[PDB]
Image 1 (cartoon, chains in turn blue, red):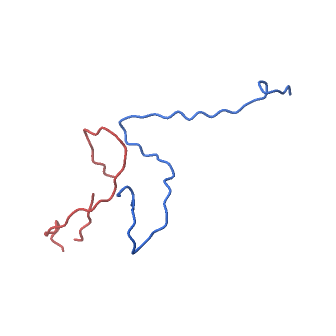
Image 2 (cartoon, rainbow over the protein chains, first blue to last red):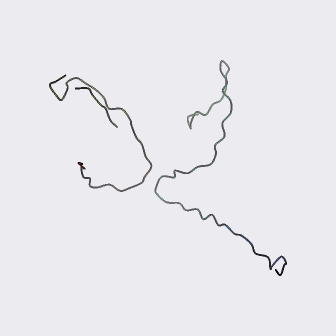
Image 3 (cartoon, rainbow over the protein chains, first blue to last red):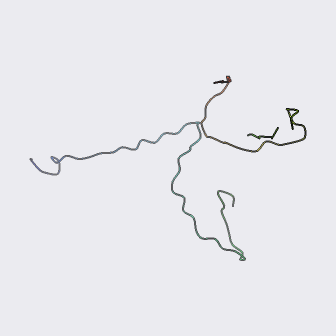
Length: 49
Length: 39
């Protein structure tokens, strides 16, 4: 019940990222746009640009 | 990759048929040996 900045309980989560030769199967939420037809546009379709 | 070819009555049908991609999984496992499983 004793309170203060250094005295209150705190909840900590640590995200420890690795790197190795195995394929990296996890990725972020790559955001898409709408589809434009019949115009000159730049495009990226699943990595093909 | 795999293909299922109907069988007619001769078994092992003749003709050219290419296998189609089925599964592509990023495991990263070093494979040197394998074994076949029957029920």
